[PDB]
Image (cartoon, rainbow, N blue to C red):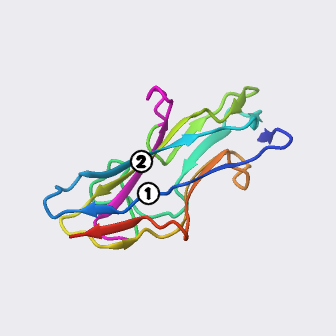
Amino acid sequence: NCTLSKGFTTVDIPMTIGTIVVRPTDPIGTVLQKNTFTISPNNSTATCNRASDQITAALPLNYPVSSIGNNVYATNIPGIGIRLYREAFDSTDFSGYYPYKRSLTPNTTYTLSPGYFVMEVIKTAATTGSGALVAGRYSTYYVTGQQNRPFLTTTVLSSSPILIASS
């Protein structure tokens, strides 16, 4: 099981993105929009004591994978998928696409690494809808037994909608 440092504090990234225009001529699989957000960690750490303990990168809205697979997940907007990941500032240390699990080394102290959180909005069908992406927590990153206290969350806010405009 995993222990968190005293004063452990989740970092949340509001995902604010301007209007994404989808055109009929955009082929299926097009990355319509790719946004990077700075991951700015604090001194929070986690230490675990069992080799079965895990770090989990999860998508709590629990939408199904889209028709095109490849970790492109459906949204409330037909034909519009999202894909999430993290990377170092120098673009290395690719986290892998959400969701994933990774085994943790017992007695290693883990921190949140700095870098970019990457959100891609991707066309997944010939016909695409219009509207705001549903608001809420789009990703979470937490250790075993500490799902209530993640290292990192990303959130779409009601007050800052991500609008899909299809023409």
Label 1: which secondary element: loop
Quarter that holds the C terminus: bottom left
Residue at x 34% of width, y 67% of height: 164
Depth order, front residue of 129/38? 38
Q: Which residue is mark 2?
A: 35
Residue at x 28% of width, y 66% of height: 79
Pinpoint residue 114: horizontal percent, then vertical percent: 59, 33
Q: Which residue is mark 1?
A: 17
Q: Is residue 147 above or below residue 7?
A: below
Q: Is residue 92 magenta?
A: yes
Depth order, front residue of 72/155? 155
User: What is the magenta range?
Assistant: 77-95
Say what amino acid the circle numbered 1 marks: Ile
Pinpoint residue 55: horizontal percent, then vertical percent: 62, 40
Pinpoint residue 15: horizontal percent, then vertical percent: 51, 55
CB contact under 8 Å: marks 1 and 2? yes
Which is nearer the N-term, disc 1 or disc 2?
Answer: 1
Q: Residues within 10 Å of mark 2 (few under 14, many from 20)?
A: some
Tell me: 66 left or right of 155.
left
Label 2: which secondary element: strand
Q: Is residue 100 magenta?
A: no
Residue at x 49% of width, y 29% of height: 89
Quarter that holds the N terminus: top right
Depth order, front residue of 123/101? 123
Say what amino acid the circle numbered 2 marks: Asn
User: Quadrant of residue 67 in the image?
Assistant: bottom left
Q: Is residue 53 above or below residue 73?
A: above
Tell me: 103 left or right of 71.
right
Report the label total: 2
